[PDB]
Length: 245
Length: 179
Ligand SMILES: O=C1CC[C@@H](NC(=O)c2cscn2)CN1
Image (cartoon, chains in turn yellow, orange):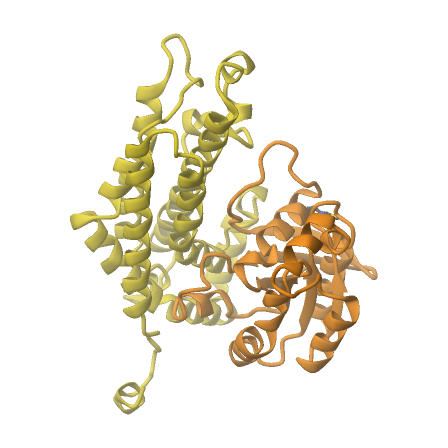
């Protein structure tokens, strides 16, 4: 993450991020809605950061320092560039909605009233098709990635030294290779929880309650399709094992 | 410090998300209770042994049977949660969550945890449950379910007041360390 965005999302809530004199100007219901939208954006910023650790720290570090066999880095980090493209674009839209809402003279005071339309756009059309295709592929390669990592860490000296070196800093404590893979797999199932709680506090404008209701339904359709398109790939599994599934 | 992995399972109403948040912060949030939990690596020292315990939630995965098992690989201890204010969450333990955890995590210790123990003597809870011919889960009902499912042990806690929370995670660490 870049310093500007980390600082904007450093507080535990929207109510602690904005000036106390700005917070006083809003009703309780608006503060509750804004705290949940802030959590959605803050966790999206962290998710994009997880993908940058996977692409820039791990993947690129292995290509530029180690002599792994061709197709090993791709097996460890399946679809990481496609995942990074989807979520960096989504994060850009979320952060631009916050930026447009800022009060003149402020870099922290804002209220986001129209999140629903952004969520409908992300979870429909070509972008939803690409999310479904990318997560169906990633989650089906999840077990194979973990197994490939375990084998390399246990048998390759230079690979083990590389992992221990880049994961040594305290800021990488929750972000080892397998932890990153599970953080990404679990991201998609966090969206309905966040959207439903934003919806619970968005009844004040009927068009906004309707847009978020449509977005929640689209997110659930996407999750059902991804879940139905998963079959764990296994290195060395024979065709007979596959067609006798 | 050896690294161990903990996963919490249970129905959406069981309070698993809140439990992980309160333990990771050593505080029940005073301003905003997060909707979700990403992950955390807690530094724990139990009976003289230092451990790095990675914590994971399964919240949001309950309706997706192919996404949910992806949280289980290499788990060292399972916390199987139910809420004391919800006898229906306890009923779903033996034939829904238990067969699943034993299949994907064979020989992994399971600790059955009764959450929201502060609501056992809450008048609103007692009045509400009485309308569906029910009452807050009794400690012996919890112990009996834990015995029945072959749990390593039975414990209770309250994320709201923190009572019992330290004890659950220190016992989970000891269980994760066993042969
Ligand atoms: O690194 C860490 C984070 C906080 C700590 N929490 C507690 O002991 C605790 C006792 S009751 C609620 N939390 C555990 N180890």
